[PDB]
Length: 305
Ligand SMILES: Nc1nc2c(ncn2[C@@H]2O[C@H](COP(=O)(O)OP(=O)(O)O)[C@@H](O)[C@H]2O)c(=O)[nH]1
Image 1: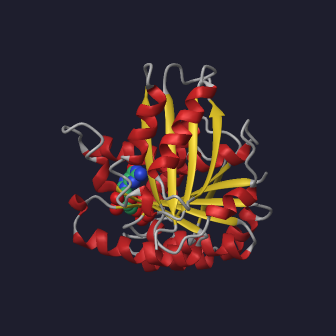
Image 2: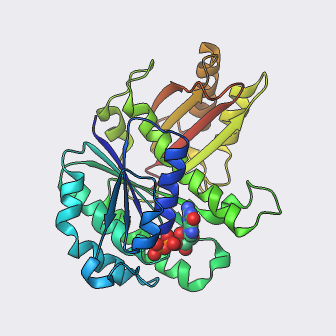
């Protein structure tokens, strides 16, 4: 009932902006940064500047230790801001300073308060270099000590989904959108009950990550749109391990007012059949008027090990 999405650092705050622009519902947004100037560019209702003393608003200089210590200075304000949450999503681009460093501390504060804590983060594009990958690897492992499940999106695989010619700015804009899909794919099912009923317990069921959780997405229009979206999702480059390996699968089928009963059963079957015969599968369905001929299938896969 109280669901918070907390964007952490530049990339995380940009994802939260995307979510706000797509008018994702049922969540309260918090933006967090060590850089006061970038924080001023956030559309989140709540704008939290961490490490005022340590950084004087000037950011974390790509250093995870400064992000970590900024969040420790601001420990009590983060506690305050997260008070009363049943569920907390922590999004960030891993590899920089504020995200890598502060997102785990924020995740752990969420968890200590009793919130169901899901992380949705990206691993950096190879083209950002070896130093970024290494800092990201470090933050990813810290993060999964601090959350109930960590969805890790490998940015390289986005290049296999967007066109050959894509400058950086645009590549990073599609990373905002995959982050948004990871959060929304879950939150949409929980914010409002749904025609398929789906409570917190259903979600806690699959919310058990040792191992990085992975996500697949599939979009389609036309007359076989259901099977084509389902198939694309279980086939997404973002899903770096076959879905048949996962202990847990959450499926979200989203469409417009003409999403059909037969399509929901079709997609549910395609995804279930590609999965292990002993899988714990929970799924839901949501209507989004803004979609017309388009359906979106999202699969979140957990418990690979
Ligand atoms: N989703 C998204 N990711 C970004 C963006 N810019 C950079 N990144 C990624 O996020 C990582 C950290 O960047 P940034 O968030 O600016 O660092 P931070 O503010 O110190 O946490 C980078 O290594 C990139 O892979 C962006 O605008 N959107």
